[PDB]
Amino acid sequence: NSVSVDLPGSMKVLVSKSSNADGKYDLIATVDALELSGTSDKNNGSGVLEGVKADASKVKLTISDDLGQTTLEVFKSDGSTLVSKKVTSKDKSSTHEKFNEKGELSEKHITRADKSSTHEKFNEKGELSEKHITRADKSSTHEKFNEKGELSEKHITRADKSSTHEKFNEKGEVSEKHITRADGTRLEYTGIKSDGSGKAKEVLKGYVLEGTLTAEKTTLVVKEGTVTLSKNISKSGEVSVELNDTDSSAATKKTAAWNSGTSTLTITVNSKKTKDLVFTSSNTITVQQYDSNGTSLEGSAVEITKLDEIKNALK
């Protein structure tokens, strides 16, 4: 007396086995703890089923003739002013729409078979205020729009959980850029001027490096005495480090050479190597001393954990 066929949207329809009075098989379903009722001339499960919520919201479920699609709409008392709509296909793709208290589109979520998704939010003028695109690898593009329809903020996340976020001022210029690396370290670019120059902070485990940003490169600076160490990061993220010492004295002046194969800075004082500073691909720094004669390294490299240790290595 009751065949139940499952529908797209994780729903079920229970249909009469045969004609009752008229040649229409009965259909009843329960969606979100509410019972729906409708009559169709087919034995599929196809047709329409209507109901009324506790707050008098009108609910209508329409099942495609071929069972491949469901459309669940929540109207208001009038049956016209929409509250919510959900369209779900057999491949489990879905569209979920929310509407404001006026029936105008407020939000729209689209979900696909691979669990990729798009989320759109709309403002009181019907303009797209936010758009979130989430790919199947969990990579994402999140955009926020100002009242003029232009970008206020853009944030891109990659599959490895690295990210780049850009904030735009009222003139369309990037004013702040924040980067979170896959390993958890971070870059903060603030006060970006109209030529792309600005202030730069690299947040590492245990310490923060500070410096400047140009469109060309980022340069972080540590100073101790007359010694300035400059850590440069290219447009490509390539790290290169240089050192300059204004020390008058030829006996005490520090010079340094950069090894691009190892990302290692070798400091030298009075013709003898003193220490190797390694800038790891893990965005850490290690320091290892040379022997008395400065020809071979000694002991084991020790990871830098505070800014003062970098300065101590520059003394």
Image: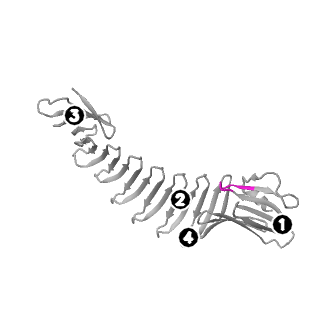
Q: Is residue 219 left or right of residue 53?
A: right
Real-space Cα distance between discs 4 and 2?
16 Å
Circles 1, 2 touching at the beta carbon (< 8 Å): no
In the displayed structure, 164 sits above or below 15; it is below
Between disc 3 and disc 2, whose residue precedes? 3
Q: Is residue 263 left or right of residue 181?
A: right
User: Which disc, if any, is residue 164?
Assistant: 2
Chain part drawn in magenta: 280-286
User: Which disc, if any, is residue 269?
Assistant: 1
Q: Which secondary structure dominates the residues rendered in magenta?
A: loop
* Residue drawn at the location 31% of the way across and 53% of the way down: 105
Real-space Cα distance between discs 4 and 1?
37 Å
User: Which disc, if any, is residue 27?
Assistant: 3
Residue 33 placement: quadrant: top left
Type of amino acid at the residue the image marks with label 1: Val
Circles 4, 1 touching at the beta carbon (< 8 Å): no
Residue 75 placement: quadrant: top left
Q: Is residue 177 left or right of residue 276?
A: left
Residue 241 visible in the snapshot:
yes
Real-space Cα distance between discs 3 and 2?
52 Å
Residue nearest the viewer, comparing 140 with 212: 140
Between disc 4 and disc 1, whose residue precedes? 4
Between disc 1 and disc 2, whose residue precedes? 2
Assign a secondary structure to mark 1: strand
* Residue drawn at the location 68% of the way across and 55% of the way down: 284
Between disc 4 and disc 2, whose residue precedes? 2
Q: Is residue 255 left or right of residue 260?
A: right
- Residue with the mark numbered 4: 196
